[PDB]
Amino acid sequence: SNAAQFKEGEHYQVLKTPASSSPVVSEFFSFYCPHCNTFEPIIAQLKQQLPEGAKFQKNHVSFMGGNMGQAMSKAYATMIALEVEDKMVPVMFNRIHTLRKPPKDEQELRQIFLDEGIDAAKFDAAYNGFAVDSMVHRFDKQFQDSGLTGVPAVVVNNRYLVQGQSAKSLDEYFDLVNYLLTLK
């Protein structure tokens, strides 16, 4: 017998973007998105069970938060640049969704980092710097080129968009991502 396989059109969609050069799982998210917050424990599990060699990369989108969406994307890229994601990702989700005190402007956004002990000079150099600017350009262009319509969204190898609702269980969802990682 031959085993059943995941199906294009039911379980995933092939996007117009080029395939990646190595295996990668990308999650498009916003800190403003409650469901993205809810998805965090599942993302942690997903990462822990990925095949050796596969990368995982969050991409922040700028379309939630009104006039603070771009600033919040810069904040996420700053977390990457400063290598403080493990602390600052849950801090930022907590600030928005549990404390429910989202930053009204870039000054308040910066203060969220300083209040966790992030060095002010390092923050200022990163937030307004070239690496962060480059990363936010990439987040936005990837979202556009991929033709995505909302968050959260999980894309494997740059061109396989997971149809999240198609999986009947978490283990099946993981199986789907692991399968897509083998496709070019």
Image: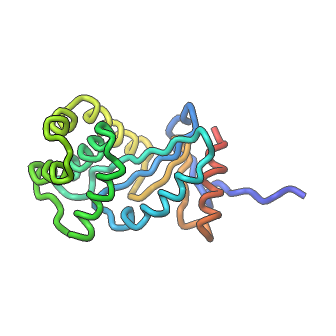
Q: Indicate left or right for 73 with 159 as reference.
A: left
Please say which color scheme the image uses: rainbow
Residue 104 percent across, percent down from the top left: 11, 58
Residue found farthest to the top: 130
The C terminus, quarter of image: top right
Q: Indicate left or right for 26 with 10 as reference.
A: left
Question: Which of the two residues, 53 or 174, is positioned nearer the viewer here?
Answer: 53
Which image quadrant is residue 4 in? Answer: bottom right
Residue 24 to residue 171: above or below:
above
Question: Which of the two residues, 5 or 99, is positioned nearer the viewer here?
Answer: 99
Question: Which of the two residues, 32 or 96, is positioned nearer the viewer here?
Answer: 96
Which image quadrant is residue 78 in? Answer: top left
Residue drawn where x is 33% and y is 40% of the image: 83
Residue drawn where x is 30% and y is 42% of the image: 77
Residue 166 percent across, percent down from the top left: 59, 66
Residue drawn where x is 23% and y is 64% of the image: 96
Residue 61 percent across, percent down from the top left: 32, 50
Q: Indicate left or right for 27 with 64 as reference.
A: right
Residue drawn where x is 27% and y is 64% of the image: 94
Q: How many marks?
A: 0
Residue found farthest to the right: 1
Which image quadrant is residue 170 in? Answer: bottom right
The N terminus, quarter of image: bottom right
Residue 156 to residue 65: above or below:
above
